Amino acid sequence: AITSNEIGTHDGYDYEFWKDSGGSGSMTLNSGGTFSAQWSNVNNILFRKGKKFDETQTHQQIGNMSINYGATYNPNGNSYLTVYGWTVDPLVEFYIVDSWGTWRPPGGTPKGTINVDGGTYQIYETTRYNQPSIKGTATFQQYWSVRTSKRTSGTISVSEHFRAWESLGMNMGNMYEVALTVEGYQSSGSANVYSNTLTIGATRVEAESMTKGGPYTSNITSPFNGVALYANGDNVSFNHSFTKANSSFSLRGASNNSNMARVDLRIGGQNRGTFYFGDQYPAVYTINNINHGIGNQLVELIVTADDGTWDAYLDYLEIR
Ligand SMILES: [Ca+2]
Ligand SMILES: [Ca+2]
């Protein structure tokens, strides 16, 4: 295990153990973006796995960034579970915080909010005066998106936070780092980051992000994150701008049991086909060659053949 400061690359990912004086820590690196960590009686500690960059590109130039993660997170004291990193020129230290210990960061008055990844994050900006940094002691801005309640797994749409910050005038520099991170302050604890995939660079719409309609539509977590349509008239819908007139649609779903489940597709109020799922194991059903014509159009997925013998579970819809 790593028990003192160290920077390196492990299985494709840039890792770092960093602490100041006082107490101890231990970090074990596992496959891909994963790692586990332990600390006690620290002042400041950071464990992370992500990507470090060469400081010549903006986040736009590098491309879309998304982290998909899960962690077991048991801090004892002040701690964060967060995406963390830096820009340079200008020097900015930044956090997208999904969970924490005893204290929810960072103090001060929010500049804004963003609703993303199924949660709500309040946005903050502070100046740090004469503080340690990747470039030595310096004065720099610190930007934060902090979830309004705790979560320890899911998807963090890093680029979307970056754009929200910029839209509020929180200017960003060239990237130095983006990493899923475990931080402790004046604390002890442990964490097991069992899943951490950083993805850099067809539209997929998650069922659980669409508008719900009908009497019973509800979110589900098994056999995937998505929604259940239980009765006639249960639906989910969203608006989409079609740029061509002809598309393929792929729905990933399942029945709740071994009876076949069916979900009708409509575009601008008109019936365009049905998706079939023959049992409880997730699968993708694809409707090809749908002529619908151009512009903003309401996409709906709705149950119309329910008879009290099955429900339809929907994970996501892909449009090509
Ligand atoms: Ca039903
Ligand atoms: Ca889903």
Image (spheres, helix red, strand yellow):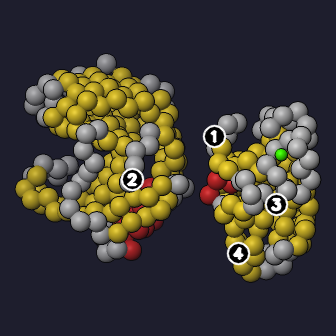
Amino acid residing under circle 1? Thr
Residue 263 is at least partly visible in this image = yes
Q: Give the number of the mark in front: 2 or 4.
A: 2
Whether ligand 2 has any atom under 8 Å from the Cβ at mark 4 is answered as no
Q: Is residue 2 visible?
A: no
Under circle 1, the secondary element is loop
Few, some or many C-alpha atoms within 10 Å of disc 3 (few <14, some 14-19, many ≥20)? some
Q: Amino acid at mark 4?
A: Ser
Q: Quadrant of residue 212?
A: bottom right
What label sits on residue 241 in the rendered view? 4
Q: Which amino acid, by three-letter code, is at mark 2?
A: Arg
x and y percentages locating residue 289 in the rendered image: 90, 64
Closer to the N terminus: mark 1 or mark 2? Answer: 2
Residue located beneath label 3 in the image: 233
* Mark 2, secondary structure of its residue: strand
Measure the alpha-carbon separation of dots 1 and 2. Answer: 20 Å
Disc 4 element: strand
Where disc 3 sits, the SS reads loop
Check disc 3 and give the amino acid type: Gly
Q: Which percent across, then down, holds residue 27?
A: 31, 25
Percent position of residue 56, x then y? 34, 60
Front label number (1 vs 3): 3
Relative to 24, residue 175 above or below? below
Please tell me which of labels 1 and 4 falls first in the chain.
Answer: 1
Q: Looking at this view, is 216 or 135 the one in front?
A: 216
Residue 147 numbered tag: 2
Label pair 3/4, CB-CB below 8 angstroms? no
Label 4 Cα neighbours within 10 Å, binned few <14 / some 14-19 / many ≥20? few
Find disc 1 in the rendering and name its residue: 221
